[PDB]
Image (tube, rainbow, N blue to C red; front, top):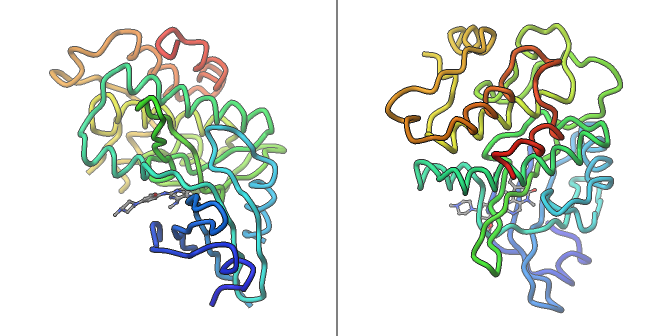
Length: 258
Ligand SMILES: COc1cc(N2CCN(C)CC2)ccc1Nc1ncc2c(n1)N(C)c1ccccc1C(=O)N2C
């Protein structure tokens, strides 16, 4: 049901992601591959995400190319990351080396640092919203996407959202939260990369009470070969104290990411 302007210039392919749907497409003039995200409309949440996607341009954030708006849906031509999401990559590989995990955290922290410099909190940083990028070198980067929950922090936020595995304890406590919930989610992800399981796993109230306690353990034998530098960084990212918890700048300054 797609407008002529899109089909005129793009050959729409298979669905690659399923509120919205994402499809593969080929730009006819160049044969270069892109992504088409189709957001269905109701008879304010879409306006917010496009306003964010218009402002965010960063090599580690999925780029918005152009918008085609019709009454029933909104069409977004977006960058295609051909690696797939990080969730599928973690399912196939089990765990990563410290060198691979540290380079991936460098990409995530770069995107978060850029977002926080705009006072944008993502609020949905998780492996399903990270995309693995294939370089010419064979090296792989990460790109952050899906800003449907992103918002500008002009004061403390209180709305509970995000996937519980990655949700910061201040969100669960409903006492107010800001940009640093993104750092906590990045800390949980880094922890998953280094060992293959989340730091807080629960049994749904068990998981929340464990996050609120925020006791990060590095169990044997899974963490025996992991460096103390990595355990220090993850610990500083997963601090319950919002003031002591690392900012994205502090994450990037840490030796393990350098
Ligand atoms: C070949 O590329 C992919 C393959 C798979 N599948 C998964 C299923 N498996 C059976 C085969 C491999 C998946 C994805 C991508 N790519 C991708 N490139 C760009 C996205 C995006 N997904 N979608 C889906 C997004 C997903 C999360 C966050 C943002 C986006 C976002 O806004 N954009 C614009």
